[PDB]
Every structure is written in C-alpha cells, then in structure tokens.
Length: 232
Length: 232
Ligand SMILES: Nc1ncnc2c1ncn2[C@@H]1O[C@H](COP(=O)(O)OP(=O)(O)O)[C@@H](O)[C@H]1O
Ligand SMILES: Nc1ncnc2c1ncn2[C@@H]1O[C@H](COP(=O)(O)OP(=O)(O)O)[C@@H](O)[C@H]1O
Ligand SMILES: [Mg+2]
Ligand SMILES: [Mg+2]
View 1 (cartoon, each protein chain N blue to C red):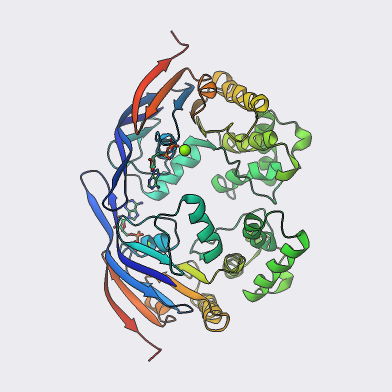
View 2: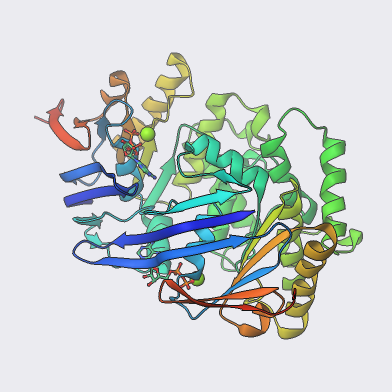
C-alpha cells in the first residue's frame, strides 16, 4: 500500500544542504504492521511526513495504495490524506472545548459536509470510539477530563473515523506510561490484525518497534537494515 | 517589524529547481499597512508563509520584530507565531462545532493554559469579537449560522486574541462579496491606524492592495517594484 522509490529529502539551510532522507527504498504491504526505528535525527518523522502526504520528496517517488502522489495538486493531495490516511501522534492534538465524541466528528464533517446527518455522525463517531476501545460513557467528556490514555484513544478513533486503510503513528506511546502505552500498541495490533489496517509506526524505543512484523532501521537519513520478526 | 534580507525559497521537484522567492528584500515598519500584489504564481502566499514562520527561507534572513527567526527551534518558532503573529486567510478556517466565542478562546487556551480563568477567556474573547466589530449577540452562534462576513470577523478576533502586533492576511476578501469585502478591509485599516497593528495583506486584486500605504509588486518570485500611495 505505501511505497517508496529513491526518495531523498533535503533541507537547504543556505550553504548547508542537509539530508534527512537519502536514497531510501521501501514497500509496505497492505495490512502489514511495520515500524521505523531510530534515534532522534535518524529521519523518522521526516518520513512520516512524506508518507502522510504532508511533504514532498526532493526526489524519488511516493505511492499510496499504488497512486503516485508526487504531482497531485494540493486539493488532490488533501483528498488522499483525508481518504487514505489516519493520523496519530505523540502530541494527542485534541481540541480543548470539544467532547471526546465531537473531536471524532470533525474529520467526518470535513469529508461528508452536507451529506451525512447529525445523527449519522454521532453514530459513526461512537462506533470508532468503541472500536478504539474507549467506554461509551466517556464519549461526552472533554480532553482534560480523560486519562492521557483515553486521550490517545480519541486520536485513534478520529483517525479511524473516515475509514482509512492506513494509519501512521509517530511515537504514539512517547507521552504515555509503559502500562497504558502497551494497551495502545495492543490496540494498533488489533486494528491491523483484525480490521486489516496497514499500520506504520515511527519510534526510537525498540520495545514499541517489536509490535511490527518488521522493523526498518533508519540511520542518519538512510535505511541501515530491516528486521523481519514474524511472517516467515 | 517584519524584515527580509536576500531571501530565496526554492522548491526541488527533483531535476527541477523552481524558484518561488528570489533574492527578495523588504522591511515593513511597525504599524504600517503594506500589500503584496501579484497574479497567482507571483510567490505571494509563499512569502506569507515565511513571514508567518510557517516556512524557512532556502537562503536569506527573516526578522520578526527585530528577532532573527532562522535558527529558532520549532518550539521557539511556535512561541514567535503565537505571540508575534495574527493569522487570517481566504479560507475562514473555523471549527464547525464551536461557538463564535469558542473559536476565539482556543488561541488563548494554547498560550495561557492553566493561568487564565474560564471567566477571563470568555471576556477577552468577546473584547476581540467586539473589536472585530461583530455584535455581541452573535457570540454564541456557530460557523454555518453566521454570514461568511461574520465568519471572517471571527478569524479576525481569533487572530487579535493573543494580541499580536502583526496580522497577516492572505487574500482575505477573496471568499467574500465587494460590499462586505470592503467592510473587512475597512476593519484591518481600523486595527492598523487606530490600534496600531502592523498589517500585511497578500492579494491579486489591486482594489484590496489600495488599502495599503504601499503595494509591493511581486513578479515570478521577485519584487518588480514598490508603490507608495500615502505617507509622503
Ligand atoms: N523542517 C526542517 N528544516 C530543516 N531541517 C529539517 C527539517 N525537518 C527535519 N530536518 C532534519 O532531518 C533530520 C531528522 O529528521 P526528523 O524528521 O526530525 O526525524 P527524526 O524524528 O528521526 O529526528 C534532522 O537532521 C533535521 O535537522
Ligand atoms: N509546496 C510547494 N511545492 C512546490 N512548489 C511550490 C510550493 N509552494 C509554492 N510553490 C511554487 O511557488 C510559486 C508561487 O508561490 P505561491 O505561494 O503559491 O504564491 P502565489 O500565491 O502568488 O501563487 C509557484 O510557481 C509554485 O509552483
Ligand atoms: Mg521525530
Ligand atoms: Mg497564493
């Protein structure tokens, strides 16, 4: 589903051409849990931004579900992200004055404006909140009234919202504790294995990378090696 | 307040190095209404992104209130945008499930978390809504219940919110009609002239550019010329 061919991403700081991704080659299978491991600076997040269609590779070529995103105009690019990708992050990113169920409704508003009813949005939003294994009785609560763990479960239901086959997570458990951090992981595993979601998680903590079928070790902008752990 | 020195912004599309801003030099005085005029492609918005601290110049140097933003880490960069800049755009950008007054509270939440009270946020939010000349009786309304004009008045109160000396507008009246489009302009004029705000507006419609003390004509990434219209 996600595919890369000779991607490079440079950052011109003037006289300093810095390379974040160098001649990187990858191919993520549909419904495959993959993890990008590396220290701060490896180029992990840069890659999560390109695959997420948040950025353009200074070379190479990105394929999302076999579709070359490179030349797509911003409008078309936004159609990709909103339909083909589900985002999650370390920084929860919830709106402070919206109920857990409202934060899940937003993406659905932006995709289906004027098509779906308030009743249908409230329903889908809950299905995704229930799917993200957050008790229904916590739907009406706002951000600061939920455990940091419950908060990530909201970012997850919001990402699952418009039903994207892809889910990218950037150091999702960085903000949590080992115990709840594992539940979230066990949750991405659930989605991938059962629901069939193509999960790609970026991390520096190897313990998280182990939930992936394969870890892709990234070093100073380049892929040092790959590690297959399961599907033999 | 805003200052540029030999800024260039290139976009590597691979074998194609495209230039959006080429060796551009500018200096906006404090409390000065300036307009960047140009056809779609001039490089206007690119410049609005750099001045807004949304992007980094591939060369040159940006000064916001005399402070060089170039080397600032993302955290420090965010402190700049949230404290020194007030954004507005053609695309209103309001959250659909939040009341006009709530959309104005958000920036204040993000800057003053845990410091200010619900009562103080509700007050400042209204002051800015009243300043943006939107009747107080429209505070409790949500987006789709306000005239497109009332909606821009919300983006304006939200921008004025954390009290930024700067206000950048990107084709603010593009989405409106001539009549209400002029009221919004007359409103930025109000802020600049009375309140003392440094207003910089990016546009392709010359009729809007005329509210500026000087128009900066931009052509294919370069400043073709400048036009002083008032302070002689
Ligand atoms: N917007 C940017 N401007 C300049 N350099 C960048 C930018 N984004 C990333 N980099 C560079 O890319 C490298 C790492 O990329 P990054 O996305 O931060 O990955 P990681 O999460 O592993 O640190 C760093 O050396 C950094 O300097
Ligand atoms: N993210 C980008 N990637 C590649 N090219 C860009 C990007 N942003 C702007 N450009 C280029 O910059 C030029 C105009 O810049 P832009 O910000 O769109 O200004 P304007 O509003 O006047 O069109 C165009 O030629 C465009 O191709
Ligand atoms: Mg990172
Ligand atoms: Mg533009």
